[PDB]
Amino acid sequence: LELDEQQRKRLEAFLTQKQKVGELKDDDFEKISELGAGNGGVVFKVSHKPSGLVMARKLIHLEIKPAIRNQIIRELQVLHECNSPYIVGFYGAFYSDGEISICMEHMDGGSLDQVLKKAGRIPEQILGKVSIAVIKGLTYLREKHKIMHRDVKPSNILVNSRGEIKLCDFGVSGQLIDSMAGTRSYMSPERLQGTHYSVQSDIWSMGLSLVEMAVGRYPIPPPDAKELELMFGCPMAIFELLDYIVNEPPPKLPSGVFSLEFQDFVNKCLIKNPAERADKQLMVHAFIKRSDAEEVDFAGWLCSTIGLN
Ligand SMILES: O=c1[nH]ccc2cc(O[C@H]3CCNC3)c(Cl)cc12
Image (cartoon, rainbow, N blue to C red; front, side, top):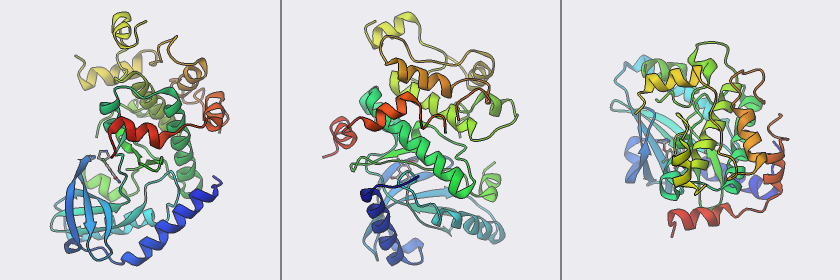
């Protein structure tokens, strides 16, 4: 988890800005626009009027007694300790007139589910950079805070015009989840069977997210030989889909379109047995080592694709 000079400096400049804000209050915010929704909430792009800082404000509507909300706010304080170039910045949390507010760093490229809608499909070299950021974010959360994400999916991966890729919406408050109490289509087979689940279930979710972004479609059930012929040249109810994840072979990338290293990488993420599934091993996988040495202009690709500007 060692940082380069540029990463260390950006992290230092975020904390210095954060120290100037102080106590977050409802009336100190002006709504600019809506960014997205949401695991039981809506996210707005806001102006924090006293400090002049543009933030992303997540609003969760919850009607509960003062007892429960005071514990939720104290449980969200753990987010002030998460400082990584792969984890979205956190400003603070508060409660006001029936709703919890989570204030965080604004990512101007939005989430990868929105980038995927625009782009159609994301190239392999760009997915290499996304894979590194997700592995490094998951490593940080586990090593420094003994927590796992539990909800890896394209909508929980944020991107910006500086070429940064960061994870958001990892559950840290037990009381907040209980009071509420999202899709289960990215959950590993062992999680859907209520069995033994570790950080291995997040690796499955990553592999699944990568296949979806590479092909430009949620990958279950697999596309037919004619669907792939349309795409590259070369309905299912949620309960049926969850049964398919548990009982059928895992999805895979089509061949002769992606490199064998990218194919091998997603196959190792998507092995149904959590013990056979790769863990440290992903960081030294051929696809990851090749992608780390590649000089990919992610910010450039992103700005051109979504029209950022
Ligand atoms: O700029 C952001 N910073 C922090 C958080 C955040 C969350 C966002 O969308 C939620 C709603 C859908 N999935 C994640 C979106 Cl679209 C943007 C941000």
